[PDB]
Image 1 (cartoon, rainbow over the protein chains, first blue to last red):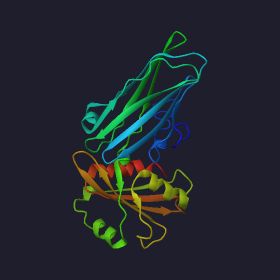
Image 2: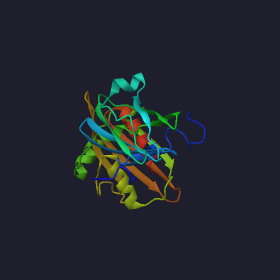
Image 3: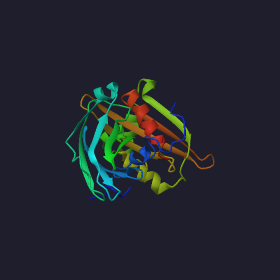
Image 4: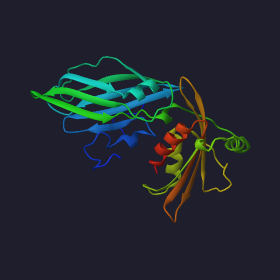
Length: 7
Length: 247
């Protein structure tokens, strides 16, 4: 899943 | 008209969450707020993450969602309780269940209030729940696109914006931004190969709005002409406004 901290 | 330096405001990074769902929405010297969300039909679920950047724990961590009255009639948000104690270096999660009742333009406000080092901390940031999140992309053949494009009746349903590019023009990025926005990116529909074409349906509890869009670049001018043709004037206006800010 995509990282909540990566953006 | 929303004046003043957009730094240390409630929306410094809002636009970064229109074409993607994850990332750091806000960050001061005590708190980090991250996101992830998913949407389906007229529903969504957003996870908000609160990171404690200090060596000290926060107390009475109270995040609240605030919507003007107008926004509350179009967007229904429900949330679960959040652990009120956040250890230093620790993270806590909040779940927001989303139901779109009708198209909306305003954004919810997320207010964070907590205790740190014996002091009261308050933070307010605009939450990136936007209309295009309820898109259902619709792939279709060229001929079908043009037939639908030409079925628009009331001029209020077409909204056009000729604006300056804020970002270097780049074909792949543009394609990526359109896909991320939510509609389908239809390849080779416009006879002018330099233009982009999209199509999708915006889903809400009370009405489904068919949506078409054309994006025209002008390298010399460093501008784009974006056109939204949908079955509801307010949807065309909000989608065009949101999409225009991305390029």
